[PDB]
Amino acid sequence: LSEIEQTNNGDTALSANEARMKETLQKAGLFAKSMNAYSYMLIKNPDVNFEGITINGYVDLPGRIVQDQKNARAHAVTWDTKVKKQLLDTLNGIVEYDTTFDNYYETMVEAINTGDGETLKEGITDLRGEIQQNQKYAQQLIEELTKLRDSIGHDVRAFGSNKELLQSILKNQGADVDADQKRLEEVLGSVNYYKQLEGFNVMKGAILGLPIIGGIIVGVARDNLGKLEPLLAELRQTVDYKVTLNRVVGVAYSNINEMHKALDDAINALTYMSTQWHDLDSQYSGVLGHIENAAQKADQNKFKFLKPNLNAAKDSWKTLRTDAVTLKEGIKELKVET
């Protein structure tokens, strides 16, 4: 075991990259808060109805839009019942890993102090096995997020064409839809937490499901009511049935479209979890090699070099675990208040 191999270096660190992992958790939380808002709205908003609406000869459009909404809702359910769960299981993996690291800690320190190489190798090997399991969780998460994103992509492009056409038809009838679309898009901005930069406080903020004419419900951050006051007043003005119809479609479109963007953003950001576990697997393999090598030395302190590494990981994994639990509770407590 060389002097260089004895430096608690980054390629053999028992710690994950704390700063990066915490950024990841924070993002996972902003993401979820957003997804839950889009899901709430999609399942809560009125079923589009073209009973007395004039479609100027595009007789197939009503069928298309209705299907667009049904496609969007099915996607929100997939998030609520499948993807969300996967996200939660993966976070629970971080917690369980810390629990295992914690449980082995005392025994590992004693092994270092007594020159017990076998115990050290066993501990690290067991942990490497837990890391590899976490690699799977993270990979499965990225797969489900990508599957859901891919699926939505095809639906939003179709929905987009249909909703643009509908807008034209209504505009052609004198509907003030271009202006209302702008207002509706601004009102819906406050719940796009996934776009936010910068602990886990952003999670405590409440989201209100505000009722607007047409049986439409818009989700707005409780602390943005004042700022959106002017727009909210406008939307509350009694309006023609044409504008109302376009709003229902517009909100549904916005929801599914923002879901697509959030997922895409979440992919680029959460993919780091897989990278991190892959790196840890390699880092722990490196540690095994150092343990094996040092085990040949006679000196009683042959494993002391691993101590600072072990101690730094002990604390790092504990902080990550605590935040992982804070995020998990934050995610489970997500709820729009109607």
Image: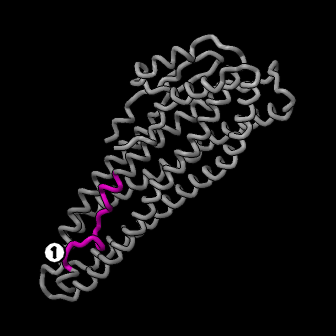
Question: What is the x, y in percent for residue 132?
Answer: 45, 67
**As rendered, which of 183 and 303 lies closer to the eye?**
183
**As rendered, which of 113 and 246 lies closer to the eye?**
246
Question: What is the x, y in percent for residue 216?
Answer: 62, 21
Could you tell me the amino acid type at mark 1? Lys
Find the residue positioned furthest to the top.
238
Q: Over which residues does the magenta segment extend?
A: 6-22
Query: Mark 1 sits on what residue?
Result: 304
Q: How many marks?
A: 1
Vertically, is 54 above or below 126?
Answer: above
Q: Residue at x 61, y 39 (%)?
A: 256
Question: What is the x, y in percent for residue 171?
Answer: 72, 25
**As rendered, which of 270 and 89 lies closer to the eye?**
270
> How many residues crowd around disc 1 within 10 Å: few (fewer than 14), some, or many (20 or more)?
some
Q: Is residue 278 left or right of residue 148?
A: left
Residue 289 highlighted magenta (yes or no): no
Question: What is the x, y in percent for residue 299?
Answer: 12, 85
Residue 7 highlighted magenta (yes or no): yes
Q: Is residue 176 left or right of residue 295?
A: right
Q: Is residue 109 left or right of residue 62?
A: left
Q: Residue at x 61, y 27 (%)?
A: 181
Q: In the rendered view of the protein, which quadrant contains the N terminus?
A: bottom left
